[PDB]
Length: 294
Ligand SMILES: CCC(C)(C)[C@@H]1CCc2[nH]nc(C(=O)NN)c2C1
Image 1 (cartoon, rainbow, N blue to C red):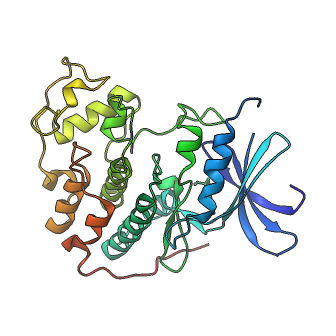
Image 2: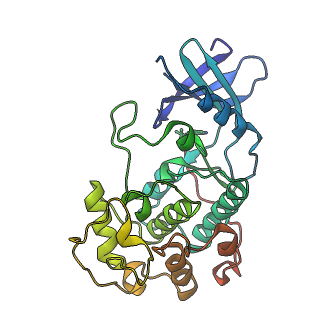
C-alpha cells in the first residue's frame, strides 16, 4: 500500500496490525488493518467484501478490501479511541449512567441492523467498540469472525479474551445465533456500570464456571437441551443463582431487568436487539457528549 502515508500505529487486532493512515489522494484519514499464507478460502474475500454494503451510523465503515501481495488490507473509518481506553480512563469516577445508557442504546441499534441482515459479530469486546467526541459509539470488526473464525491467540500470540463469550459457544454449540452478540453486549453493559469485568475467565472452564457461579448452573428447566450439548458434563458443580441486585449495583430495576434478559441462558429466549430497544430502560435515553481529553 503506497497510497497511504502511515501516521502512527493504532494497535494490534485479532488478525493483523492496524495503522492510522492518510489517503495520499483523497486526504482521507483512515484506520488501515493489514492481515498477513497459501490456502486462504476465497470465500473469505467474498464474505468480507460483502460487508462494504453493511452501512449504519453505529457500525464502523469498511471503506475497502484489498487482497494483494500475500496480504489483506481492510480500510476502516477512523475513530477517536476504543471503549476499553475510555472505561479505564473513567475508572475513578465511572462513566455517567446517561452516557452508559446512550452507548448501550446505540450499540443495540448497530446490532439490530446487522442481525436484520443476518450478519453477526461473534467476538464483541470493549476493544472493538469505538467512540468519537460527539457521543457516538460504533461496532468494529463486524463479520470478520465468520470469514476467519475466532482463534485461541491473535497474530501476535496474545490470548483472545473469553470474558464476553456466550455459554452456548463454551458448551460446544455448532451453530451460533444472533443471541451470542446480545450476551457479549450484556457483559459489556455490566462492566461499564460496575467498572469491573463481569466474568473475567482465564480459561474456558474458568469462564464457564464464573458464569455458573453468578447465574446458577443451567439445567433442563431454564435451558432445554443444555444437558445434550457437546461439552456439557453432568459433573459440573451445581451453583445457586445470585440476585442481580448483587451483580450490578447500583443499577436501577429497569437496567437490571434488561441486563437479566440479555443474559438468559437459553439463546432462543435471550432478548433480541430489536426487543431490547423497546425496553423501558430506554424511556429517558439521551445523547450526552463524553469528556475526552488529549
Ligand atoms: C476493532 C479493533 C481495531 C481493529 C483495532 C479497530 C479497527 C477500526 C478503527 N478505526 N479507528 C480506530 C482506532 O483505534 N482509533 N484510535 C480503529 C481500530
